[PDB]
Image (tube, rainbow, N blue to C red):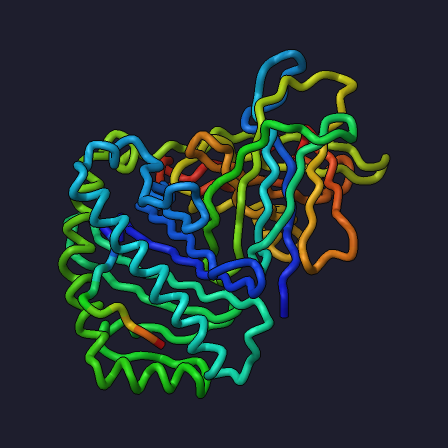
Amino acid sequence: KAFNPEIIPMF
Amino acid sequence: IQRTPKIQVYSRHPAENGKSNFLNCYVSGFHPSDIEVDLLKNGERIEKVEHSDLSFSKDWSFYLLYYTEFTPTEKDEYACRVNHVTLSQPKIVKWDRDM
Amino acid sequence: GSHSMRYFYTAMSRPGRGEPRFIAVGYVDDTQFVRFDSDAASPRMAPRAPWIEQEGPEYWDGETRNMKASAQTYRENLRIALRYYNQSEAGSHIIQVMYGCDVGPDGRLLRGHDQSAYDGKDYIALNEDLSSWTAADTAAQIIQRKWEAARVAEQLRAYLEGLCVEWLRRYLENGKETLQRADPPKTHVTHHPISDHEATLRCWALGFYPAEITLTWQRDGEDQTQDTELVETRPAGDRTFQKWAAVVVPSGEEQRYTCHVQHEGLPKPLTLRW
């Protein structure tokens, strides 16, 4: 199962 | 800066003339990911060629397997033709059944 | 450590040719089990191994939703990277990411991974502590500051120590017949004269899984590291791998050479001669 953060990290 | 593809052409099983097999062209070590690969039978493009999903190695270089069913014979010549940004013209690697 | 799960994402800009393509693949060890391609007719997370097929609609819909959100985020990261490197909107660029977990025989976390590249060069990496970052350059240091401020490492750590290992363990059980089976290499040596004075000895390993293998030639018991031609380990297309190692030997000295093969599927290392 893939990593699924609430906020996906932006550069 | 950009990395040119390494190319191996080979069969899934040891070749037996008249016995159905798979012809593989494995392209690896390249960057960027856009790449053109044809499998050739006696200089002409084989239509039914499948490939793996784009993946990459620990050094970030990409790899792909291209493959087609074939039945090798004594006289039929097989090759893989590859084009990539790093290449001035398509590179053609002939299948050698001993490599 | 006995098993790994890894996800690999590639995001590729192509100005003038639509939005950046996003491809994701997932692996357990050397076995691909899922893919996603934003260019597909109907993009979904899709099975690539039989043991994942049993997962229900909730699994597939959730993975698809995640991939679509990820594609959008990586399109934004490609735009941000342009600003960080003073690059124009005219050129094609690539972001790559790899993450996942390694587990030992007892299924506990051995180590976690999360690494990014830009244009094929290291960008930023989560350190082995799963708490701090290593930035490759001043651009990645900007990202590092943002991720420190937002406690991103803690989020990755929670996944890597939790869901990553739990789902890996599940897949290993569901795929026990293949994922927990090592296939040892079928080995042989071939001999190819090149002239009256020299011949190639080629040591073959075929049909093995997983891909990790060591092939070494010795002359009179001494490893021929500098003089051995080793091809990259290559997939056969049936899950297994192939490799060979070759040495050029003086004719009449073939019996002084021994090929040594180490692989997880072998009870002990093999020694071959021609």
Residue C239, image quadrant: top left
Q: In this view, does B16 lie above or below B33?
A: above
Q: Can residue C267 be seen in this view?
A: no
For image coordinates 56% across by 56% down, the residue present is B33
Q: Is residue C250 or residue C124 the one in the foreground? A: C124
In the displayed structure image, the side of residue B7 where residue C13 appears, left or right: left
Residue B49, image quadrant: top right
Q: Is residue C229 or residue B48 the one in the foreground? A: B48
Q: Is residue C188 above or below residue C198?
A: above
Task: Tell me the quarter of the image containing the N terminus of chain B.
Answer: bottom right
For image coordinates 22% across by 70% down, the residue present is A7
Q: In this view, does C159 lie above or below C238?
A: below
For image coordinates 16% across by 62% down, the residue present is C161
Q: In this view, does B34 lie above or below C157?
A: above
Task: Tell me the quarter of the image containing the C terminus of chain B.
Answer: top right
Q: Position of residue C267 (x, y in %)?
A: 34, 35
Q: Position of residue C26 (x, y in %)?
A: 34, 48
For image coordinates 51% across by 64% down, the residue present is C13
Q: Where is residue B26 in the image (x, y as percent from the top left)?
A: 58, 42
In the displayed structure image, the side of residue C131 where residue C90 appears, left or right: right
Farthest right residue?
C196
Q: Is residue B78 or residue C143 the one in the foreground? A: C143
Q: Can residue C202 be seen in this view?
A: yes
In the displayed structure image, the side of residue B35 where residue C6 appears, left or right: left
Q: Where is residue C148 in the image (x, y as percent from the top left)?
A: 25, 83
